Image (cartoon, rainbow over the protein chains, first blue to last red):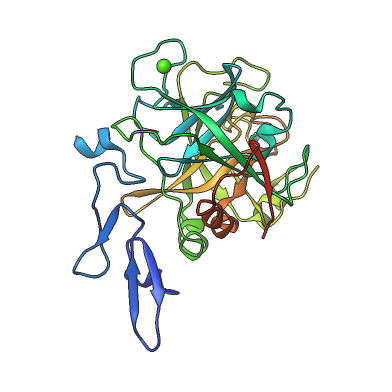
Length: 55
Length: 250
Ligand SMILES: O=C1NCCc2ccc(Cl)cc21
Ligand SMILES: [Ca+2]
């Protein structure tokens, strides 16, 4: 599943028994209910530029 | 950085400045509040191990504006496979004595998971390379942080396009062969940052080349994807006496 277009995951992808796919996020992020998107859980998550995000 | 631009203050918030006896040594990449990724070759001639400082939130070297945070380097971890004076396995993992405080000007770059980095980030063409290195080959170094956009090459295309050490599976080429744009020797240890779906990731470390922006040559970067597990296991370890530590690789 993860082999093709990162399994739809915005960040990390895990393959499971059958057609089951689990998207995952880097620490400082939480997975949204769409099961593919990652939302920051912290003020300064990794790989985001605050001055660019704030404007 | 050759043929790039000033990185606007705060737009490279993971950039690290490495200092020895207060003098400019190399660049680095903040990957969390305690750990910095740099190049192993940066520590080849270090004698004063206790006088290593990492500065975060740096921009302009001539003025202190209050966004700078300094930390003493507690440990420098280098792979057992790296041979001083050579190009292969050019990675160093640095432990800060105390964590940096994240602010608008101090933010880590994401260390990606291996598979994601190999299958997805490896195919993002352009990435950003940054530092306070030489502005020209045999030129003055920069006072303000510089940034350059570079395209990545498959090792086969790099070898064919290049006019001398081998490009191993632990390296990748990025840049231009026209002599206009490149990272330079004072940029060593700095990031090669890849953007994917609104987030930036660490994919390479400024490593080596045949002179900066040399016609018929590309910049060579450490392939960080080969080191993720090595890095992850080390970040889970307790520090050891002595700053320099040689850890087995794989
Ligand atoms: O001469 C160089 N050309 C390509 C980038 C580079 C990086 C780091 C060092 Cl030491 C030298 C160079
Ligand atoms: Ca400054």
